[PDB]
Structure formats: C-alpha cells, structure tokens
C-alpha cells in the first residue's frame, strides 16, 4: 500500500488495479558462473629470445589457447598503448576472448597512439600487410640505459621509401625501394633509388625511447565456439531444474544446468536462434550437452478496493509459477492473498483470462468463468403472437469532446 | 548550466536538449497531431449527430438513444456538448393467436395494415405496435386469388 | 517492454550512467499501457450489445428453412458452428519482452454471438428496442418483403421455392469459404506485420547502433565508461525510434484499428438488429437479414439480398 | 573440358554448433553453374579459382588430391607442394619442385596445422591459419559430375604462416574434376533438423 | 528516396562508416512503399 501511494504521488487511492516496481528473480544463488577452463600463458621465452629479428623477420612464440586474464591484460599499468579498440580496457576484465594470439613488432614515438596489429608505417606495409585497425597492447618498463648504438641502427629502419601506403602484420624480407617513380631497384642504393630504409638513430647518449623496446603484442578473437572457454567465476554442479548460480560462459543470471537432449546442429554453438544466445554447451571434461535458460521475471501488480473503506491488499505476479517464488495459481500468474469462491457475479476489477475480483467484509476474490447475464427463453410456437398495451417515455444523456487547448 | 559550462562540453548538452525537447515533444508533437486526429474524429461525429437528430428525426437503429426516437435538445459544457434524447418504449404484453389469411367465399383475404388476432372465439384486426381491436370488413382487406 | 533490463542487461554501472537522463522509461511505459487498455475497450464495445442470454427452442419447425450450418453444435467439446470451426482451422520472449493475455476468451465470444443469433431468429427486430415478443417466420419474412415495396402475398405464394433457394445458397457459401485460401488476407496481414516489427525490434540488438558489435551483453562486457555512454545513447535512441515506430505507426495502427472497430459496431447495430435503407451499406441488392459469426481477432457477416432476374417490354 | 560446375565446393565457415535456420554469409566460395577451366586430372592439366578460393576440386575415389601454391612456383620464393592422403599425417606443407604438366610425387617447421566416393579437398591461408577440409560419401556414377550437393567439413584449425599467391596442380598417385570462376558474392545456406547443409543459392547469378 | 546515395554521395569511406548502424534504411524504404501502394488503392476504391 505504501508502494502504490508512492507511485501515485498521493495519499488517497481509488478502486482498481495498479502497477508497482517489477520483480526480477534476484539471484537465489548469486550472479556467478564461468566454465571449466582455467589455463594461462607465459611470456619469458619470447621476451628473452635471442632474436627479435628485423622488422621483416620478427620472431613469434606461441602464446595462445589459454584463458588469458584480460583483467591482467588491462590492469597492467606497464601497457603504454591501450587504444586496443573493438574492445575497451576498463571493461576488458568482464570479457571472454576465445583466443589471444602472439604477434609482435616495434613502435616509434609518434605512433604510440597508433600501435596495434594494424598500425602506422611503411615499416609495416612492406614488412607487414593488413589494414590499419586498432587492436594491440604493448608492454613497457624502464628502458633508459639498457642497449643502444650511437649513429643509427640499420635494423630498425624507418622505411620512408616504400612504393605504397601503410599496412601492418604480414612478413616480407625484401628491403625494396620507393617506387615514387617507376624504378624497381631490387634493394640497392643510387639516385632516385634512395636507400629504402633510413635509421631512426637509436643512440644511448640519446633519450630513453631510443634504447630498446622489445614489444610483446596480443591478438584478440571471439567465437561462438563450444562454450568451454571464457573468463573466471565459480562453476556449480549440473544441478538440473534448480535455479542456481549462472553467469554461463559470459551469460549472467541465476538458473539451471539442465542436461540437453538437443543434438544441436553443427556451426553456431552459441546457439544462434535469432536472439543469438547460447542454448547448448559441451565441455572437454563434461562432454554432455548442457542447455541454457534464465530464470523468471515479471511485473508486480497490486489490486485494492478504495482506501477509504479498508486497508487489505492482494498482490499478483505476472507470468510466474507459484513454486518459483493463500496461494492460488491462475492462467495470468500467481495470486497471493485471495479466497476462491464458486458462485459467479458481475465484474468489478478485471484481472485477466475471465477472472475478476471484489471485496467482502460482498463477494470474495472470485476466480472462474464470468457470468454474462441473466438467462432467458422465449416461448416459440407457430401460431402465437404477442402485442403490447401500454407505453413509457424515457430520457438519456450523451457527452462528447469537441475541442482542445491552444499553446505555442 | 549555461553559467557553469564550457563550449565543447556544452555543445553535447545543448544538442541533447534540442533532441530531447523535440523528442519528448516529438512523441508530443506527433501527439499533438495524434490527439488532434482523435479530437477531429469526435468533432465530426458530434456535427453529424446534431444535423441528423436535432434538425430532423432519424430511423437508424441505435444512433440517437435506445428505443424509437422522438426528439432531442442540446446543451453546452466546457470544451464539449451534451445531448438529451427522448425515446418511446412498450410496456405490457399479452398472448394471442394468429393466422395468415381468411377464406370466406373461396377467396383469400389479406390485411391491409395490421394482423389478424383472435381472443379465443372471434377475429379482429389490430395495428402491430399498439393493441386496439376493430371489426373486420372489406374496407381494410384486399382480395388475391383462391 | 522493460526499459532498464532491455537497455542495460543487469549492469550497475550501466544503470548509474543511465540515471542522469530523465523519465524516458516512464513515458514509454505509460504509452504502452494506454494501448493495452484500448484494445480490450474495442472488443467489449463491439461485441457486448445485449443484456440477457436467449436460446433456441429444442424443436426446429421454422417452416422449411434449415439453419443447421450456423447454430451451435453440441457434439464438439467447444460449442462452435461448422463454419466457425472451418474459420478457426484456416488461419495459422527473454530480452525484457512480454505478452499479456486478453480479458475475454473464445468461449465467451461464442456465447455472445449465439445469444444474438437465437434472439433474432426467434423474435425479429423487437429485442433491440424493448422487451422480446415472439413471432413466426413466414410472418416475419412477409414483413421484411413488404419493407422493400413488394406486396406481401408474393411470399405466401412462393414459400417452398424461396426456402429451396435459401438452403442452396447457404451450402454454396460454406463450400466457397472452405475452398479458397486467400479469404482472410486482412487478418493474416495484420498478424504478420506485428510479428515482423517485433522481430526487427529484437534484432536491433543484432544491429550495432554505433557499436563495433551487436549483441549487447558482450559489448557491455567490452566497453569503458566514455565509450559505453556513446553506445547506449544511440541504443536508447534506436529503441525509442523503433518501439516508437510501433508507438508512432501504431498510434497510427491503433487509429486504423479504432476506425475499423467503430465501423464494425455501426454495421452490427444497423444491419443485424434492424433493416437498412442505405444503398450498398449491408451488401449489394435489397437488404433482408444478416447473421454474425466470429473469427480470431475479427468478425464475419453474412448478408441476404433480393435480386430481380427477368425482364419484358411494355408500353 | 568445360562443364557447368553444378553445386560443388561449399563448406562450413566455422566449426561451432548451430540449429535449424536460413542463414546468409559473406566469404570466399566457388560459383554455381560456372564455366570452369576444368582441365582434366588423369589429360591432367591445371584448374581455375578466381575471387577467393583454395584449390577447389571434385573427386571419385581420392583421385584429385594435391595442388601447388606459391608466387613464382619454382621454389625460388614462396612455393608450396602438397601430397595428400589424410591417413598417415606427417605434415608436408614443405617446399618442393613443381611442373607445368602438374603432377605429384612422394624445411616446413611449425606442426600446428589445420565416382565411388566424394572427397573434395581445401587448402586456404587465412590469418596464418592453413585450413583444410575433406569429404567422405559414396555415389554410383562414373562418367561425369553428379547432379548433387555436399558440404566440406574441416580436419583441424591451426595456423602456420606462409604466404602464397599463385598455383599449379598435383596428382596423388599410388577424367573429370570440376572447379569454378567467382567474384566475392554472398550465399544463402539452408539446414535440416539434423544439421546438414541441404541447399544454397548464389545471390549474383540471375534476377 | 535513394537512401544510401542521399546520405553518402558516392564515397567508399562513407559507405564503410555507415555499415556499422543497421537496417534503418530498409525500414525507410518499406514505409514509403506502403504509402505508395495505399494511394492507388484509394483511387480505385473511390472510382470503380
């Protein structure tokens, strides 16, 4: 009653059925579940590899097929370039990347707002090839006095002379000229063949940035795959038909690990019925197919007579089975605080599916097929007629709106 | 807001303000147009009712009242109008016995306006909407065939 | 539709950033509720036009006419006429969407229509004005014939021929309604349009709306504050524009449905409960009598008319 | 020769698990009713692919299995030779010698790899992945292309990272095989309740 | 109305930027087609 007084913004309340704040199934057990997979990945043998060979022969160690701690992948303040787009850092923790691969390259000072698989450089487009899209995040610690060479480094070589534009992450070792005209110089020097790669000048007497930056990058891939791989959260037992913790492989809620008989045909396991939500899951250790379904939710509506006659109130939950929350189950939901009766009357407060309700200290909160009117029957025979003998005069009343207000 | 704010951060808020004013106000100017459509429908109905029921007498069933229409009187109200309808209603019935025709001299006699009714021993002829009996003659019957 | 659940998907941060906009969700809920009430108002207004519940006598002696193809059939568990059965058989959830059940059920609709039909058959046009007064069919049909300027002995000299033509026509219309599949195009089109609009309003989640992806769950587990706001403002814009393409096109569509319901109510009051003199209103020809029937989200009328057929010259 | 390629060379864009829809996808395929430069395999010359294809193929009893990739196809640069049996998988995506009478005889580092029978092969290179797809189902005709349909299922899915541009043919030795000519169009796959691609239409063929 | 043409004006960059939004444009075409059919329905119904 206080809730509906708040909703109507008054104290007096008339007779009818009003709606209040809805009821979602708050987690009967908390909002937590993520799959069995728990792997991780090292970086040592790629960060200490003898050769991060030249930009055209960059080295790669297999860092993939693991549950990468995307929180660690963004909570790391050592990450200088984090315009790792498509996804976003501060919510990277809540994510589920199917795979996190391992490619690498070397950055410059002006590109730190441009660095990713997909980045800026003719460096890229001739030692690399794909579009310029942002997804790639760079480890960096203090490298002020580590390793550098006065005069210029002829390995990390800004390829100002490249026949075309900038496109990263492929490989090609041909140190080839600028085709600013029409000259294929086959990787030699000359005039109008200006040596295709100049040196930034990574000098140790120079600043920190010149001294070495061995960069380990990480690719990102999302799949509708068999929902075995996702982030961390406690996985409950396959307690079928009981609303338990589930954030199933990323799909939050609270609900059921119901074993599924669905053969679940073969290439959108994140079952892409047009809603595109997982409807079956298999796991390497639990090979069984596990159905997915969230628990209930629905509005809460309050029925009440006038506030000047009584303070009793009944509550109806819409489209909720009673066991999942006097209790009485109807076709419109679960009704709490009522008395079932068998005699039928007219309708006062319409509920739904042919049920009404009213107040008794006259009728109970009735629930059955309605009464449509008083039954009658006309004595019909093939030689009889009926004729009136008196008349009456009546007066009725009709009301109609004709106009409106006038504003600007 | 205008006193406290800065320009490229106030641009987003003024853009939002026009969008929301024209949006709440766009379901609401769409709603001025929608409610205007509804009010226009009601106004047309009222004009038809006046012309057909106050300036004349109508035969359309259940258009002006319930029963048989006789008259109407209008009144006035704030942003509206009110009608009073005068009708006619039958009261008290009584059973009788009927027949389609009468064969007096081998000929068939049909009523002109009314019905043949019999109180049990004799035959009369009455109008349909009110019970008044009359004797039966060749004034109010016509002949057709055998 | 549930505004908060649909836009945020149970995210405290999303709700907190959304709380600084206003009452958009309140207005949307108010509009949807208004439409929901209007629908039930429509159905009640069209169908509930009688106060009592009449019923036919057990003995069928109507002078030759056969009404068996429209009166209720007791054999079925649900008392529906064979024409109603043919009509009913002819025609063919989780992202905050709900559907509510209607207030009147098919059984109550059937009872109302049966009451109308039995009343008119037994007592003519006198049960709409005052009390019910009985009368036989040959006399009632003589009155109807006299209503269109033909002297009333013509009926009495042709009773058997008229009855035979009536029965043949009833059989023919039953067969023709059964045969063709394109009779109920209006109702089918309405249902199809509504379902399609809802499908797109869910698949705009499968749209992006400024987002690099579509499915809002993973994008919300993806995006930062200053970019998540960029996504959700366009998402609410699109949901408001689409549910309000329904709200706009469907305050429009409720305007269409309201016009149709008003027309149906007028047709019932003037063709079923009386006799009409307006040309081409209740059918083509000279009007005699009408019978109603029900159908899913609609109503069906069967008119009866009189047509001259053979001409000769004179001076 | 030159024949209508009928409805061959379709596959699964991913190895995931769907159910009972009518979908539409955008990827690199093989045409429907193509003017294939089908040069034979046994009378054993090269094939076409056009806009985005592996060495698509047809097959009778594992007859048409191997093909060559590369850019100059002389082992002087990126160059690839593939012997194919799919039984004793000791991977040879290694670098070998080729021919313009293209036929198959009896290094490559990273072992992280992807008419009486129907076994069409696949050899792609997408983002380092060297995807392969095979087949297995028997039929009866012996002369020419069966008028039928089938979808190719993957073997593994793992990347290696070797570039390729051009191609020749090979012949895995102890008549007819059909390919197509495409441009990057879209397809409309169809499914049953048991989950097998049953139909497809090419959106850029006719009105 | 030629939807994409009006918005972009023969620009590949505009096309690729627009492909991130959805089926607004199909919706617009659908509504206009409905109006176009209704007009001829009205004229026929009045006159024939």
Image: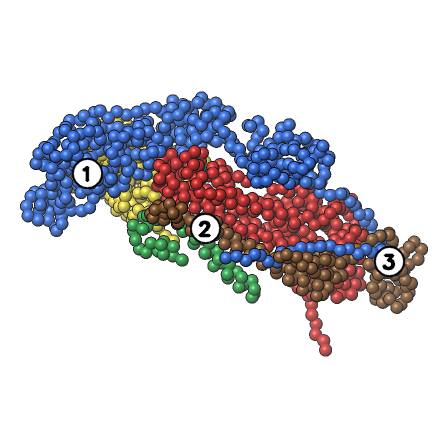
Q: Please determine if labels 2 and 1 lie on a single subunit.
A: no
Query: Relative to A222, does residue E39 appear above or below in the rendering?
Result: below
Where residue D21 sits, quadrant-wise, is top left
Q: Is residue A360 left or right of residue A70?
A: right
Chain letter for the red part: C
Kindly identify which residue carries mark 3. B131
x and y, in percent, of residue A188 in the image: 7, 42
Query: Relative to A101, does residue D39 appear above or below in the rendering?
Result: below
Q: Label 3 neighbourhood size at 10 Å, few (<14), some (14-19), many (20+)?
A: some
Q: CA distance from mark 2 to mark 3?
A: 70 Å
User: How many numbered circles does the render carry?
Assistant: 3
x and y, in percent, of residue C85 in the image: 64, 44
Q: CA distance from mark 2 to mark 1?
A: 46 Å
Of the numbered discs in the image, which one, if any, rests on residue A109? 1
Q: How is the image coloured?
A: by chain
Q: Is residue C310 left or right of residue E13?
A: right
Report which colour depicts chain D.
Answer: yellow
Q: Is residue D130 visible?
A: no
Report which colour depicts chain A.
Answer: blue
């Amino acid at each position: 009653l206080s809730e509906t007084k708040c909703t109507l913004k008054s104290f007096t309340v008339e007779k009818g059925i009003y709606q209040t704040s809805n009821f979602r199934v708050q987690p009967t057990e908390s909002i937590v579940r993520f799959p069995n997979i728990t792997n991780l990945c090292p970086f040592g043998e790629v960060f200490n590899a003898t050769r991060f060979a030249s930009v055209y022969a960059w080295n790669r160690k297999r860092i993939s097929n693991c549950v990468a701690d995307y929180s660690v992948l963004y909570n790391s303040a050592s990450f200088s370039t984090f315009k790792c787009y498509g996804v976003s850092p501060t919510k990277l923790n809540d994510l589920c990347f199917t795979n996190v691969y391992a490619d690498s390259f070397v950055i410059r000072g002006d590109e730190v707002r441009q660095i990713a698989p997909g980045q800026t450089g003719k460096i890229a487009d001739y030692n690399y090839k794909l579009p310029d899209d942002f997804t790639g995040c760079v480890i960096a610690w203090n490298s002020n006095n580590l390793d550098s060479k006065v005069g210029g480094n002829y390995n990390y070589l800004f390829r100002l002379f490249r026949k075309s534009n900038l496109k990263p992450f492929e490989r090609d070792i041909s140190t080839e000229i600028y085709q600013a005209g029409s000259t294929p110089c086959n990787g030699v020097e000359g005039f109008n063949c200006y040596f295709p790669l100049q040196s930034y000048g990574f000098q140790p007497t120079n600043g920190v940035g010149y001294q070495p930056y061995r960069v380990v990058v990480l690719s990102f891939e999302l799949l509708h795959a068999p929902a075995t791989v996702c982030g961390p959260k406690k996985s409950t037992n396959l307690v079928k038909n009981k609303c338990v913790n589930f954030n199933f492989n990323g799909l939050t809620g609270t609900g059921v690990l119901t074993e599924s008989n669905k053969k679940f045909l073969p290439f959108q396991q994140f079952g892409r019925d047009i809603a595109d939500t997982t409807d079956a899951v298999r796991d390497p250790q639990t090979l069984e197919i596990l159905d997915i379904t969230p628990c209930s939710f629905g509005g809460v509506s309050v029925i009440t007579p006038g506030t000047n006659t009584s303070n009793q109130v009944a509550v109806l939950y819409q489209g909720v089975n009673c066991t999942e929350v006097n209790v009485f189950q109807t076709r419109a939901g679960c009704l709490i605080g009522a008395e079932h009766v068998n005699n039928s009357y007219e309708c006062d407060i319409p509920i739904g599916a042919g049920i009404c309700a009213s107040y008794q200290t006259s009728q109970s909160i009735i629930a059955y097929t309605m009464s449509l009117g008083a039954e009658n029957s006309v004595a019909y025979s093939n030689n009889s007629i009926a004729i009136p003998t008196n008349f009456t005069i009546s007066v009725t009343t009709e009301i109609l709106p004709v106009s409106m207000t006038k504003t600007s | 807001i205008l006193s406290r704010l800065d320009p490229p951060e106030a641009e987003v808020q003024i853009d939002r303000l026009i969008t929301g004013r024209l949006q709440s106000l766009q379901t609401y100017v769409t709603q001025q147009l929608i409610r205007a459509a509804e009010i226009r429908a009601s106004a047309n109905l009222a004009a038809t009712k006046m012309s057909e029921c106050v300036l004349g007498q109508s035969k359309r069933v259940d258009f002006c009242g319930k029963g048989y229409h006789l008259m109407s009187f209008p009144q006035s109200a704030p942003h509206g109008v009110v009608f009073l309808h005068v009708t006619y209603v039958p009261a008290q019935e009584k059973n009788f016995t009927t027949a389609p025709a009468i064969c007096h001299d081998g000929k068939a006699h049909f009523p002109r306006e009314g019905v043949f009714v019999s109180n049990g021993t004799h035959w009369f002829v009455t109008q349909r909407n009110f019970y008044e009996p009359q004797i039966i003659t060749t004034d109010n019957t016509f002949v057709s065939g055998n | 539709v549930d505004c908060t659940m649909y836009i945020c998907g149970d995210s405290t941060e999303c709700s907190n950033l959304l709380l600084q906009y206003g009452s958009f969700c309140t207005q949307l809920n108010r509009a949807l509720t208004g439409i929901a009430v209007e629908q039930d108002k429509n159905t009640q207004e069209v169908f509930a036009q009688v106060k009592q519940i009449y019923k036919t006598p057990p003995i069928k002696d109507f002078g030759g006419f056969n009404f068996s193809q429209i009166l209720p059939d007791p054999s079925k568990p649900s008392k529906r006429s064979p024409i109603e059965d043919l009509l009913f058989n002819k025609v063919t959830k989780f992202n905050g969407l709900t559907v509510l059940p209607p207030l009147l059920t098919d059984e109550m609709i059937a009872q109302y229509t049966s009451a109308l039909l039995a009343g008119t058959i037994t007592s003519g046009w006198t049960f709409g004005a005052g009390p019910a007064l009985q009368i036989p069919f040959p006399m009632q049909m003589a009155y109807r014939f006299n209503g269109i300027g033909v002297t009333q002995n013509v009926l009495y000299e042709n009773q058997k021929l008229i009855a035979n033509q009536f029965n043949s026509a009833i059989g023919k219309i039953q067969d023709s309604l059964s045969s063709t599949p394109s009779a109920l195009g209006k109702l089918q089109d309405v249902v199809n349009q509504n379902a399609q609009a809802l499908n797109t309003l869910v698949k705009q989640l499968s749209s992006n709306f400024g987002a690099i992806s579509s499915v809002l769950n993973d994008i919300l587990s993806r995006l930062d504050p200053p970019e998540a706001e960029v996504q959700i403002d366009r998402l609410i814009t699109g949901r408001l524009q689409s549910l309000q393409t329904y709200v706009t096109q469907q305050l429009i569509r409720a305007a269409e449905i309201r016009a149709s319901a008003n027309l149906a109510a007028t047709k019932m009051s003037e063709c079923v409960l009386g006799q009409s003199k307006r040309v081409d209103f209740c059918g083509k020809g000279y009007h005699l009598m009408s019978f109603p029937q029900s159908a899913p989200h609609g109503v069906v009328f069967l008119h009866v008319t009189y047509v001259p057929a053979q001409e000769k010259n004179f001076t | 020769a030159y024949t209508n390629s009928f409805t061959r060379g379709v596959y699964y864009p991913d190895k995931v698990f769907r159910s009972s829809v009518l979908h539409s996808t955008q990827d690199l395929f093989l045409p429907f009713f193509s003017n294939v430069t089908w040069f034979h395999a046994i009378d054993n010359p090269v094939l076409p692919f056009n806009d985005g294809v592996y060495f698509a193929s047809t097959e009778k009893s594992n007859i048409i299995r191997g093909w060559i990739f590369g850019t100059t196809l002389d082992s002087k640069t990126q160059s690839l030779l593939i012997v194919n049996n799919a039984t004793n998988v000791v991977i040879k995506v290694c670098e070998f010698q080729f021919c313009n009478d293209p036929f198959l005889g009896v290094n490559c580092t990273f072992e992280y790899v992807s008419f009486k029978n129907l076994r069409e092969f696949v050899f792609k290179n997408i983002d380092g992945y060297f995807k392969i797809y095979s087949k297995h189902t028997p039929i009866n005709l012996v002369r020419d292309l069966p008028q039928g349909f089938s979808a190719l299922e993957p073997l593994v899915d793992l990347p290696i990272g070797i570039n390729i541009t051009r191609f020749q043919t090979l012949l895995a030795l102890h008549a007819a095989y059909y390919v197509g000519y495409l441009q990057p169009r879209t397809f409309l796959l169809k499914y049953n309740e048991n989950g097998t691609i049953t139909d497809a239409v090419d959106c850029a063929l006719d009105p």
